[PDB]
Image (cartoon, coloured by chain):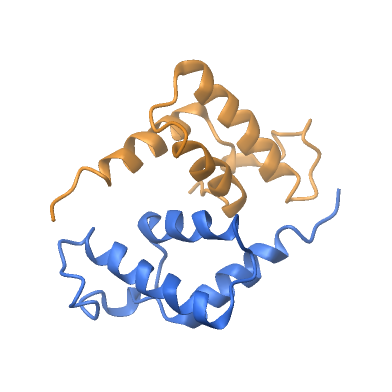
Chain colours: A orange, B blue
Amino acid sequence: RFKWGPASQQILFQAYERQKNPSKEERETLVEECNRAECIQRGVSPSQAQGLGSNLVTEVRVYNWFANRRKEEAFRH
Amino acid sequence: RFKWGPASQQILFQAYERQKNPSKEERETLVEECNRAECIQRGVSPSQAQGLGSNLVTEVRVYNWFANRRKEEAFRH
């Protein structure tokens, strides 16, 4: 289990179109920005970002989203 | 069943931030643009947009995505 929220996804798509290869440090910003945006939807305080539980955006998942979204431009057609 | 593809979602998020209240006619453009973009990921021809099956973006689903994404700005905090 673990799913991207529509709240974290518009953060993430907004980003890819300025840069689809986020650096080490960029990736870690998008993680803050995903957890918090996800918290303030759940009527959860940003400081209790661990309130999310399994749905906590680890930076590996931000990495893979970019990786995998780049795969989807590596196509046919 | 029926799910939004990451291909249809970046089409759809790209749109909301120019306009979150798409008109009758706009909605029907985003439907074309979602099915086709979804086809060309599946190594399916755009003309066989019915190849998709259940995952065919009806314009009601485009309507509801906008509706529901607007709900998510109607918050607390």
**Residue at (73, 51) in percent of width and height:** A41
User: Which residue sits furthest top?
Assistant: A25
Q: Is residue B50 above or below residue B30?
A: below
Residue B62, position as x, y percentages in the image = 50, 73
Q: Is residue B24 above or below residue B73?
A: below
Which corner quadrant of the image does residue B48 belong to? Answer: bottom left
Residue B27, position as x, y percentages in the image = 50, 76
Q: Is residue A70 left or right of residue A74?
A: right
The answer to which of B48 and A48 lies nearer the viewer is: B48
**Residue at (30, 62) in percent of width and height:** B37
Q: Is residue B76 left or right of residue A56?
A: right
The answer to which of B32 and A53 lies nearer the viewer is: B32
Q: Is residue B54 visible?
A: yes
What quarter of the picture does the N terminus of chain B occupy?
bottom left
The answer to which of B51 and B59 lies nearer the viewer is: B59
Which corner quadrant of the image does residue A32 belong to? Answer: top right
User: Which residue sits furthest right?
Assistant: B77
Q: Is residue A6 above or below residue B64?
A: above
Q: Is residue A16 left or right of residue A33?
A: left
Residue B73, position as x, y percentages in the image = 74, 57
Residue A69, position as x, y percentages in the image = 35, 42
**Residue at (33, 79) in percent of width and height:** B54
